[PDB]
Image (cartoon, coloured by chain):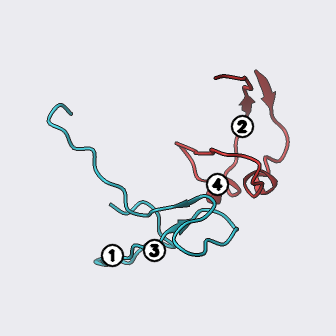
Amino acid sequence: RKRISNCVADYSVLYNSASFSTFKCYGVSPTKLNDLCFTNVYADSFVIR
Amino acid sequence: YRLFRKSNLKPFERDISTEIYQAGSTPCNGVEGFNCYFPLQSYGFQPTN
């Protein structure tokens, strides 16, 4: 678990990249993500089958 | 039901379009593309629900 805060959570370089396969947001939308402000974002990275 | 639209529809408006939807900057030519989703999604109605 890594805490991300006090920065700009840009996603243009994230969504536009085609190197990813599946990317779904069940609570928000990428279009309105830019105009949305977050307090703290935690990134949990793991490798699974 | 319709899940994605270019903009909010005016009151008492019917949208029967079946054209695919693009959720990013990349173009969506033809009937499919990268991150191209069909705007019409079925309903999961079951008696057990």
Residue A49 appears at what percent x and percent y?
A: 64, 23
Q: Residue at x 76, y 21 (%)?
A: A1
Query: Is B7 left, or right, of B33 in this rendering?
Result: left
Q: Residue at x 78, y 57 (%)?
A: A12
- The chain under label 4 reads A
> Separation of disc 1 and disc 2 at Cα?
40 Å
Q: Nearer the viewer, mark 2 or mark 3?
A: 3
Residue at mark 4? A30
Residues at circles 2 and 4 in contact by the CB criterion of under 8 Å: no
- Does label 1 lie on the same chain as label 4? no
Counting other residues with Cα less than 10 Å from the Cα at mark 4, is it few (<14), some (14-19), or many (20 or more)? some
In the image, B36 versus B31, the foreground residue is: B31
Q: Residue A42, located in which quarter of the rendered image? A: top right
The three-letter code of the residue at mark 3 reads Glu
Residue at mark 1? B16
> Separation of disc 2 and disc 3 at Cα?
37 Å
> Separation of disc 1 and disc 3 at Cα?
9 Å
Q: Is residue B33 above or below residue A30?
A: below
